[PDB]
Length: 102
Length: 146
Image 1 (cartoon, chains in turn cyan, purple):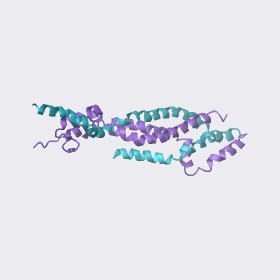
Image 2 (cartoon, chains in turn cyan, orange; image 1 turned 120 degrees about the horizontal axis):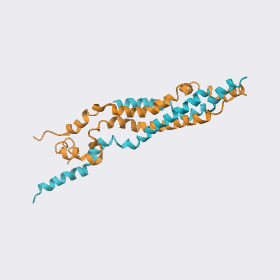
Image 3 (cartoon, rainbow over the protein chains, first blue to last red; image 1 turned 120 degrees about the vertical axis):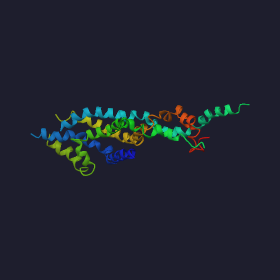
Image 4 (tube, rainbow over the protein chains, first blue to last red; image 1 turned 135 degrees about the vertical axis):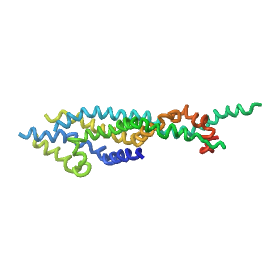
């Protein structure tokens, strides 16, 4: 139940950042421009300060992709409990080895 | 009268050992939400406009700066070319996070359930709860558990 709720917030944030994948270049020079006119008539704060966060954002992103190594850690419990029947019967096949004592 | 089935035991490891450390998964979910939060962190003060550039400022605020904010201008070049591509990298790392989170966010929260039955999780040690304590546990999985 809580697995879908977080994914719903993820999917919502995934679908409301749909355009930003190709619309994030708007700040490449507007961040520069929307200071340029005012200072030189006769915005850098967001540009400078955010550079610190990206390193923290990257590290947070690092854990997002580092967990992809652990992507096969949880769902296997239900999967391993069924697909391993070849070895499951094998361990109980030596059980059958005991019974046919002749 | 072998009517005992240890599938409860296989789930006894599963039923509530997840809640005994219910906050292990939330630490990882914080890490998964960190990229969401850090993207929200970098979309806070100046990229607050991006929350409405996606909807309303799409065709207005992008192009006015390229002329008006430089016609008024002609100390405004250095940090824009360094952070925005990193922000664009964040968006690139966000859609791939979302693809990952569509297949990883369930993992960390679920994996606390097999915390105690990590043997049942791992391949080389699920057999005991599928073969060894299973001569009655395999009754519900009668076709599987021969």
